[PDB]
Image 1 (cartoon, protein in one colour):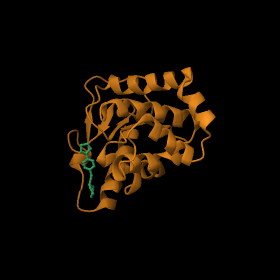
Image 2 (cartoon, protein in one colour):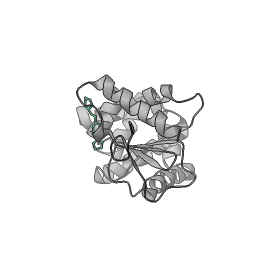
Image 3 (cartoon, helix red, strand yellow):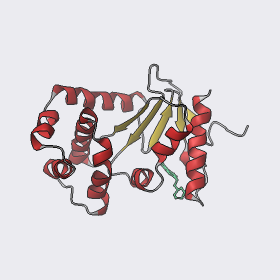
Image 4 (cartoon, helix red, strand yellow):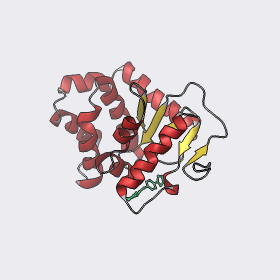
Length: 188
Ligand SMILES: c1cc(-c2ccc(CNC3CCCCC3)cc2)cs1
């Protein structure tokens, strides 16, 4: 077939009931994730190829970056709780990988302050049980699939995108193949 298990996608030997329709995992330490955000715009190009109103979910992971990796998962929980993901994603990626100015939880907080989140609101969220629950939710989603590596995308709790099997000579051809694969998997 044109789409084959092992080529554009793989199939989970233990499928995950109840998972979000489109679920992405990333780390602010991950070099491909940086490109998926700033240069390839993978999430938006997938969204535009799926029907209106489909749920897409994006979670951070702990396994890169030690202490700061876990701090970034908690900050991503804050960003989700406050609905400011679009305001902090690029400065967090650049602070971790480009300028390397993010070395502590305090440096992470500065990114939110610079983006216009008030300090009192950041701190209240950071320490809230709503955020502790969002951290647990991110861990649980990743654990369900013994998540190996990022960037990872899962479709309907059943299929995992395989970007290693896609074109790499042209950025836009790769993005197109990736998004068309998501569409194909969503229609299975
Ligand atoms: C987990 C994810 C990956 C991966 C492998 C390949 C890609 C596509 N990157 C290229 C780089 C730029 C030109 C076209 C696409 C993106 C991610 C390897 S391991």
